[PDB]
Length: 124
Image (cartoon, rainbow, N blue to C red; front, side, top):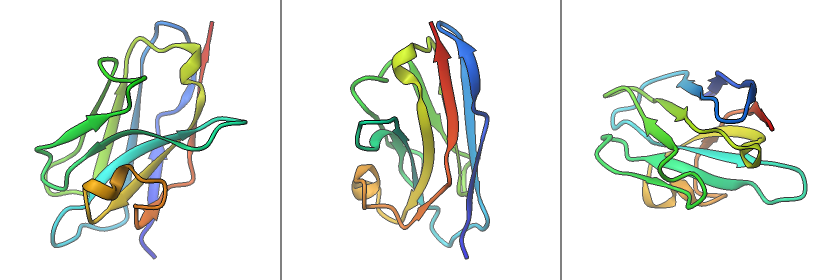
């Protein structure tokens, strides 16, 4: 019954920015760690970024570090991904995910809940 709904995807020229958003259908007594992953054809869905329930800890995949920023609203199960300096290599369907554990939130099978995906395409 928990639902995660992503928004903010689009088709944009290289070098440009997008901001993805994700809101869960409820708050939890401890806010969930949240994460973004991305999937493109021919490649396993990959971890992009995560943030702890309390917002104090973040980590990024090697390919996006320095360009993307993950943030959340304090005490809500929402999460954002600000994507700057977009490259064609960033084209994928981006999924938000929620986990009651920050350490496993970057594992393909860690999170409890998954969104349906928002497409992001970066043209050259």
